[PDB]
Amino acid sequence: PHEELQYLRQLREILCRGSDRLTGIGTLSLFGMQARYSLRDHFPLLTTKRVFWRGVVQELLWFLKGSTDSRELSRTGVKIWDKNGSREFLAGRGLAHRREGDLGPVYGFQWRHFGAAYVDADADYTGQGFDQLSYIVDLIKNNPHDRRIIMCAWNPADLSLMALPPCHLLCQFYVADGELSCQLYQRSGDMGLGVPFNIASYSLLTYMLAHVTGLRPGEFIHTLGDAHIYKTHIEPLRLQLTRTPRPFPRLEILRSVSSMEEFTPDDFRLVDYCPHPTIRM
Amino acid sequence: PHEELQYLRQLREILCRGSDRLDRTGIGTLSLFGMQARYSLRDHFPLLTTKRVFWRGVVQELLWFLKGSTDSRELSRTGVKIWDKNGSREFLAGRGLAHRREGDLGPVYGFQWRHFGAAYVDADADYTGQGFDQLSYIVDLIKNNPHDRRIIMCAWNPADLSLMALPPCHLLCQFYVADGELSCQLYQRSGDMGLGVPFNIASYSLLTYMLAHVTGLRPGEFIHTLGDAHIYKTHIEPLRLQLTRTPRPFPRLEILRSVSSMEEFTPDDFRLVDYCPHPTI
Ligand SMILES: Cc1nc(=O)c2cc(CN(C)c3ccc(C(=O)N[C@@H](CCC(=O)O)C(=O)O)s3)ccc2[nH]1
Ligand SMILES: Cc1nc(=O)c2cc(CN(C)c3ccc(C(=O)N[C@@H](CCC(=O)O)C(=O)O)s3)ccc2[nH]1
Ligand SMILES: O=c1ccn([C@H]2C[C@H](O)[C@@H](COP(=O)(O)O)O2)c(=O)[nH]1
Ligand SMILES: O=c1ccn([C@H]2C[C@H](O)[C@@H](COP(=O)(O)O)O2)c(=O)[nH]1
Image (cartoon, rainbow over all chains, first blue to last red; front, side):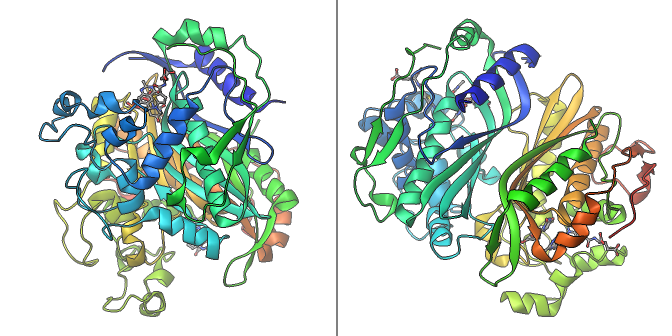
């Protein structure tokens, strides 16, 4: 039974039993969902519609950098954070005095410098705040059965400095039988666009962490809070609800990388990815 | 089907195929990673019946949390001693926390809920207007923007971990409103299925009843998401016994008078009817 059917059943449920609720734009939604994806023999990149894999990779490395600069992601060809880094959008957020591309203390800053005072995207933060990436990497290496291997992006005190508050709040990691697993808690999930993307991101993070630590990829567990469908997306989502999953691709890591920071997009080969055609939403 | 059978199934799964691990202090647990159970709050209250749950503790401890107290001496005064061991002068010394008055647990749940991001100095100090008051934040959201997808309270603060007596188990809870009902999901990084988890279920269910009462809504669903779900090997025998017990119907919870603020609840506003658990083990 294909694991992608979990995602497809969740879609089907939200569309059929979801709550119909409206500030700006309207959605169908359910609350509390969990799905499991094996990482042992394949990589759970959804096949019912093509997922922007190039975006997935560039954005994770950009996160892992600690960068909060939407321009630096943009330079690589990935424009998904650009609407949010415009001086116009920032102004609308009451953050007008930002330079272009300064998103505030978003994921990268929270992952590498939690609790630090944010100044701007160009400030040097070395040795400031709590480095969560170094923290979990050390625990996975030297104390793998620890129950506190967590990386959290939710920092309520920093919300008003943020262009957009984080959706995927925290990940926890788990080690058993030489396998590295990961649970992601996502407060909010757009099933039409974000959620396939998000599944891929944290699955990737786990492959990367597994590699760097000498472990094999295990399970990725996806726990949603608000799982929702935007109503404008209903006829394209019914389209994808008709399609049968193709087998998952595999993910190869093309070289020895000793540090989470030394990865490059060319270290990853996506083998045998054959999605159905892209659906625009 | 009776909801407690979710918990008991989880017990059995862990006992049957759980992973046999040791910590770096040598103690053995069986554990599994990634679990979710749903408990209805509408017609009843999910206080577990196959073993008696310390309900007096549940109530006093939560009221204690909601006040922002990080003083174990205060909870202990009520006759509830569950945090006394962690508050002892010797425990804190064992943690490497000198200059600590007895009962000073550090920036734990209460401090995080009320003053997230604030500079902790001590349990007696006064933090008014320091940090981010998450409790007011969520009560406000549930009242004035119930469909917000960021109705979050979080206790995981990486920067404060070395200052805490114990690191938080309940990382965060999220709330959700639909069709006149308040719902809640909790992310728990670590659950002792033997002692902690029944208690923990009662705690956040109770919190949801209180929030529902204060905001003019009916208790909806409580979703319980776990990370490391485990059983200490020493308790396997009493748990075998527990698993033979047939669950009895859940009690109910009546809130006596009208309470207008989350801070004005007293242990007396709560009527538990009728809790008839199998004998304690
Ligand atoms: C309403 C909303 N839903 C989302 O899913 C969402 C996601 C992000 C960030 N994110 C995690 C994204 C992942 C993928 C994206 C995207 O734009 N994909 C395009 C592909 C672009 C292209 O043509 O190359 C798409 O397929 O529409 S955006 C930001 C705001 C959002 N807003
Ligand atoms: C290893 C471990 N497991 C736990 O479950 C745990 C729980 C807490 C805090 N906690 C969340 C607790 C919930 C319930 C508790 C308890 O001891 N209840 C007693 C009541 C004692 C009495 O009635 O006098 C009991 O149920 O027997 S303690 C602290 C450390 C822990 N440590
Ligand atoms: O990584 C992401 C980022 C955003 N979103 C979606 C979820 C919501 O539909 C919207 C964010 O809006 P709020 O939930 O923050 O209001 O974008 C995702 O699914 N994944
Ligand atoms: O509210 C609580 C507090 C603690 N624990 C348990 C979980 C673990 O067995 C232990 C905490 O140890 P660590 O997870 O921190 O190692 O206590 C709970 O189940 N619930």
